[PDB]
Image 1 (cartoon, rainbow over the protein chains, first blue to last red):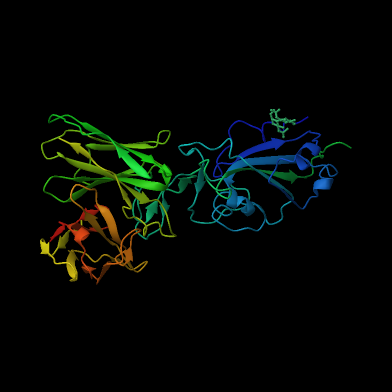
Image 2: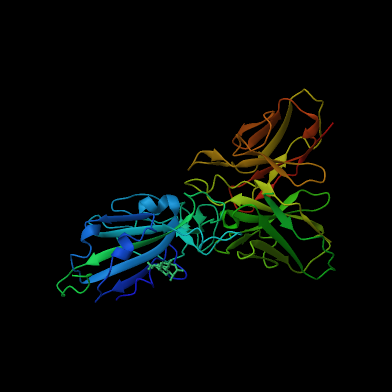
Length: 194
Length: 123
Length: 112
Ligand SMILES: *[C@@H]1O[C@H](CO)[C@@H](O[C@@H]2O[C@H](CO)[C@@H](O)[C@H](O)[C@H]2NC(C)=O)[C@H](O)[C@H]1NC(C)=O
C-alpha cells in the first residue's frame, strides 16, 4: 500500500551530503518485488533477515536515498570507514536494516559530465550516526583563520562527481537506499502480508 | 582531444570591457580549479585570478580586484572572465590554465598548471 | 607578495653541455607543515603556450624528457639541463605558490 515508488523509481535522487529521508508507517509492504526484483546490484541486510522481513512488525521505517560512486557502495555498512562513511552518511554500530544499491549509469550520466551530484570530503570531526550536514562553511586546515575566503589551507568542503558514460563500472553512479526500522513503545504499524 | 577551447581575438576600445571564455573538452570540468594568466607583449606572465567550479568562489590579485569578474557554467562546462575599464596596457594574450582540485590529503601540493589553453589576444 | 628574481636573463647554450638557471625568492618557499618547497618551472616556446616542466622543486611533469632536473634549497633554486637539446630553446619561468598573489619570475631566455 505504501509508496515504494517515491523512493526507488523516482525522477531525480539527492546527493549523498544531503540524503533524502522518507518516513513510512501504516503499510503492508510486499517485499517479493524487492528481494526478488532481479534488478539490484546489492541487497545487504543486517540485524534482519530478507526471508523474514515480512515477519517482524515495526513502528516506523525510514528510507534514506542518495547516489554514490560505485566503489563506495561497500562503505554503506555498519562499522565502516572511508571518505563517504564518516563525512557524508554513516550507519550506526547496532544497525538493523537493509542497504539496496543498483547501477544508474543510464539515468544519472551525461556526455558533458553530470555535475549536479556532490559529496563532502572535509569535516572537523566525524559524523555521529544518522546525521546530515549541509553547511558550506570553508574548512579550516592551517592555524591561520580565514573568514570565508578560499585559498591555501582553506578549502570548499564539497566536490562533484565526474559521471560520464565511458567511465568504468567502479566509477559509475549507483543509487543507494537504506531502510532502517524503528520499534518503540508506540504500537507496531508496518509489516507485510501475514 | 583533451583540450581547452578559448574565444577568438577581440578588439576593444579603451574604457570598454572584454569577455574571454574557456571551454573544457575531454575531462571533468569540476575536478580542476580554473586560473587566468595573461602575458603582455615583451613582459612576463601575470596571474589574474582563479575560480572554483564547485562553489563559484573566486580569488583575484589585488591589482585586478574590482574589475575582473569570473563566472562558471557547468551545464556547458565553460569559465568566463570579464575585465572592465580596459586600458592600453591590457593588450595581451590571456591563457586559461587548469589546476588539480585535490589530489592528496593536503590539496595544496598538486596545484600546478598541468594544462594551458591556446590563448586569446585582447587589444 | 613574493617577488622572484631569476639570474641568467640571457642564457646562450651549446648542445651537449649542462645549463643552470638560478631563481631567488624574497621569502623562503619551504613550508614547515609538510616539508615541501613550492616552486614550479615552466617553459614557453615561441608562439606556444607555457608547458609544465618541474613541480614541487624536485618532480618532473608528465611527458617531460629525462634531460631536465631541478633542485635547490631555502630561497636559491636551480633548474639544470644536463644535455641541452635543440628543442630546449625558449623562456623559463619560476613560479611560487605559497601566498596567493601567485607570482611568476621575470623569465630566462635560452637560445642557441
Ligand atoms: C518503477 O517504475 C518502473 C516504471 O513503471 C517499473 O518498471 C517496470 O516494472 C515492471 C514490474 O514492476 C516490469 O514488468 C516492467 O518491464 C518495467 N518497465 C516498464 C517500462 O514498465 C519498476 O518496476 C518500478 N520499480 C519497482 C516496482 O520497484
